Image (cartoon, coloured by chain):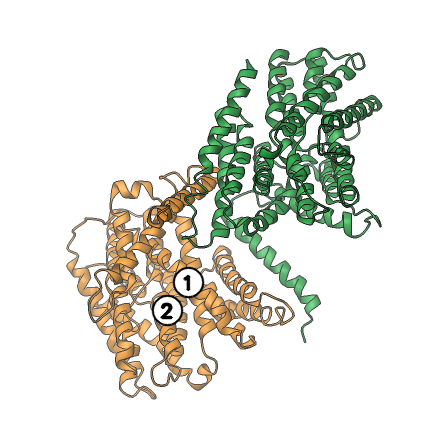
Chain colours: A orange, B green
Amino acid sequence: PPRGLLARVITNVTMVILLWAVVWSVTGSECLPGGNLFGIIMLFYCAIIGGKLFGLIKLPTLPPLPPLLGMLLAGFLIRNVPVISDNIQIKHKWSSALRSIALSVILVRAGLGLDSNALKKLKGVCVRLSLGPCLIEACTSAVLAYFLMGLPWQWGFMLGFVLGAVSPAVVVPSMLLLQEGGYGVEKGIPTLLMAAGSFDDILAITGFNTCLGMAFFNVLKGVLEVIIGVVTGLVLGFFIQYFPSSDQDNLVWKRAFLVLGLSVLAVFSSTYFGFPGSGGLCTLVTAFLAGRGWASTKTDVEKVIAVAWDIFQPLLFGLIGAEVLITALRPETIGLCVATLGIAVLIRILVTYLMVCFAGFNIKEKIFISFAWLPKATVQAAIGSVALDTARSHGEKQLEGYGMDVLTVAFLSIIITAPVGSLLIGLLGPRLLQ
Amino acid sequence: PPRGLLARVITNVTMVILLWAVVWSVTGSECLPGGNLFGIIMLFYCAIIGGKLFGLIKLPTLPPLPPLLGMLLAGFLIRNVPVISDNIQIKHKWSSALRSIALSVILVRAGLGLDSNALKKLKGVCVRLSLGPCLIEACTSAVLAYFLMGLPWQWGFMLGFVLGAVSPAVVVPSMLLLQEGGYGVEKGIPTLLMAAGSFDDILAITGFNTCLGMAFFNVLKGVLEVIIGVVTGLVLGFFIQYFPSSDQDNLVWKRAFLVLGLSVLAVFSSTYFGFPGSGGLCTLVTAFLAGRGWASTKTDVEKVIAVAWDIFQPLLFGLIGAEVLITALRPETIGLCVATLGIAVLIRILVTYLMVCFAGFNIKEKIFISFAWLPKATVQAAIGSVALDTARSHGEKQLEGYGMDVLTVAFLSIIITAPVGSLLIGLLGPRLLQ
């Protein structure tokens, strides 16, 4: 009599090797332990098992253990071991492309899940929260960094823009899960945070690019990117609410690919044209415009996108933590960098609390919004790599040394504020605004 | 208001180009019109539309037009036009690999649909039908060709083996439709023809290889191929009836994928090792062992394999008909080749009729069996291409001319007897054994 315990494993093993051989025939060395495709699958599995372990094995009693910490730790262990990192290697273009795709997935889901009429009721708070804390934190961090490390204003201002950048990837999943359940009456608070933390990305890169050029105009170029992004999103919006009608079938599957596929294509086309970052605004506008014109087909396509986002979630964080090979063990008095990021994070809490004292937020809503700007994600990692690449083209040792310090504080910030911030908002949601 | 008729096409077009752009990013090449992957998709679509046109627009009134004729014409047009020959091209390695995969699909489906206890009731007639008419037809064709074309016995014997060959790639779909429909009482007649005309490929290639070596031992090697195939099939048979059990879930998809993958792996492993054709019998034995196990999910997985076979059927015919550019317009007294082909077909009818006069087949069954061995398939094309490759390595003008003549008659035979034979058996099914 066959045994189910000894038959499930055998069947799965045979299926895996059979599928492995098929891809090996069409690719070759990629499926070999040393290759790109093999590394992506192994990194995907490593991130999956890391998330499961962090939350089901050693989870804390009262606060559930978020999988974000496990994903970053899994990527850190993979890259920071020469024998392990030898087999799994990923090209820079694939890492950048996967980052752009995953970032587009979380943005379109936020726009699709955003509630209408929220902008009309309160738009000033969203604009002030998008511009206010980002500029104040960058200035305060630059001043705090100045006269402490010795680097000039060109490096100080550049570090401030990189350090202050709210990341949609780490906040949107928290808001949508909270919004689906809901505590009390959600008066647009989840929509306010989701929309506000999107325009920040454009300003952060625009300031970073302009400041980088000074260390080597672009201010007007960034404005054109915002204008183009709105126009491109608006044009694509009318072609998703009109061509797909009730006459067509398979509405759930057909239109989910359409909105997601155009979102990915828009970002790559904008980046290839010469003005990156306009795609991030285009997908949000396209998703918001589509929701305006959907025939109550919101939750139908939300489930498909949610599954797609859940797939890319381990993949996105795995790439972020798998690029710390250079500074694996380089003790260079990192305590000073901790103080610089810690003060700026502390200032970030205070300024965000101040900006939400106008109306509506009486007592508890101020605290939740202030703590919702803690986590950081790929946005810092992408610009940080670009700064290193520009530095290591015609720069001498001093420029290389300064660039290394920027990487250390930027990587450390993602290690600290991302899992703690995501964990804090998860447990404080049912404990602050219920 | 949007119009569904004018929007469905637009939605489909946008989806296709968006999906096409995704492949462009993943694959650095093969996406342009000059790529081989683009040609595969075009050939697949051209064969699909060709089959639909031949049978739904200009179909004859009483006899339905089979799609086999349309597939051959569609492939012929693509290759036989100079401006449509260089823009779209397909490499030889992919064509050879796809032929083996398509051949494996029809073999496993034929074995799965085979009726149990059919071999035990009458196996002598199956062996005689497999060996008798095939060898006699090859000998008669060589003698008939001799004293007519002037080629020596080395070329005459090789032509006879290539000309005389029964392939299940065409007859099995006709038999399965007959089995599914049912007329009167089916005493294993469809299964008898499928089983007898399944392992004849091994004998055909063994004779071709033996004759090629003499024209440049193999008999002993061919016997070993049969022995290895039976042993591999027997061992693999117990691994599909035991490991996949009712305890697991999604048996329909899991078992169908498992048998398809193992069949492909066995054929590729045998071909790469140095003895091609052994995997052809191995999948038949493996399917027979799976059929004898009686998993009770035959019809559940037959539909899935039938859909897969229906997908690969235009692809297999498209590759065969896309290698006729060499002999597009070469008038070299082809009437003699037609006469030799007609006599060989006439000889095949007589010998097949003689071998089915033992028992059971009273009047109508003899006619059906004789007409069931007329259609031919890729078996001739594969060996014919090998003969051309061997000829064009150290051969002079006379050998080159002889090799071209062998291809012309072989290509002509496939063009004639395959669609006419398939059409003839299709209309005679409900009119002979009713």
Q: Secondary structure at mark 2?
A: helix
Give the chain letter at badge 2.
A
Q: Position of residue A315 (x, y in %)?
A: 37, 55
Residue B117, quarter of the rendered image: top right
Does residue A7 lie above or below A283 as drawn? above
The residue identified by callout 2 is: A173
Q: Position of residue B306 (x, y in %)?
A: 61, 47
**Residue closest to the eye, B192 or A58:** B192
Tell me which residue sits at (56%, 28%) in the image: B277
- The amino acid sitting under disc 1 is Trp
Tell me which residue sits at (42%, 45%) in the image: A15
Q: Marks 2 and 1, Cα distance to the nearest angstrom?
A: 9 Å
Q: Position of residue A421 (x, y in %)?
A: 26, 69
Compared across the picture, whether B67 is left or right of A407 comes to right
The residue identified by callout 1 is: A309
- The amino acid sitting under disc 2 is Pro
User: Residue A217, can we see it?
Assistant: no
User: Residue B353, can we see it?
Assistant: yes
Tell me which residue sits at (51%, 47%) in the image: B256
Give the chain letter at badge 1.
A
**Residue closest to the eye, B41 or A159:** B41
- The answer to whether marks 2 and 1 mark residues whose Cβ atoms lie closer than 8 Å is yes
Q: Position of residue B32 (x, y in %)?
A: 60, 45
Does residue A11 lie above or below A334 as drawn? above
**Residue closest to the eye, A157 or A28:** A28
Residue B174, quarter of the rendered image: top right
Earlier residue among tags 2 and 1: 2
